[PDB]
Image (cartoon, rainbow over all chains, first blue to last red; front, side):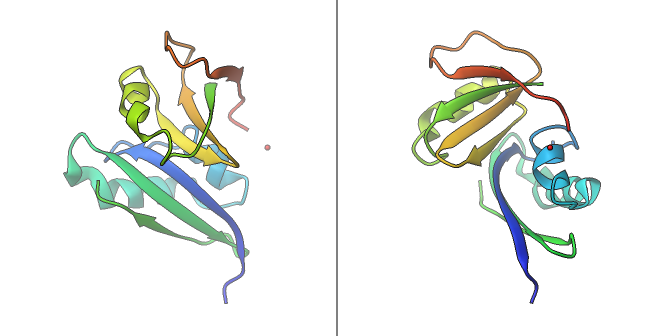
Length: 72
Length: 58
């Protein structure tokens, strides 16, 4: 509906996510597309400058994900 | 990678989090009552968190 397999609660520097930890292992263990999240998070936050951004990623059984950020 | 493990939530530890990034943290992950702060290598911090080495890849 979809079925949730994990929720991942991070804080990441705005615009500056990479596939490295915590992102790689936190998402990858559930098969979520690491690079897609990196690019999406960076698009969602690059224009925030030097901020630290709370982000929650929900990962589903089909390996898709959704996410929510908080400003800032 | 190294992790600095601190008891607490991101909310509870909020005041010291910018200092972790200033010290070189690449990102934070809240996990069951703890904050895991990821660093390329250990650094000088006053908090008495636990240093643990982690592989990239569960």
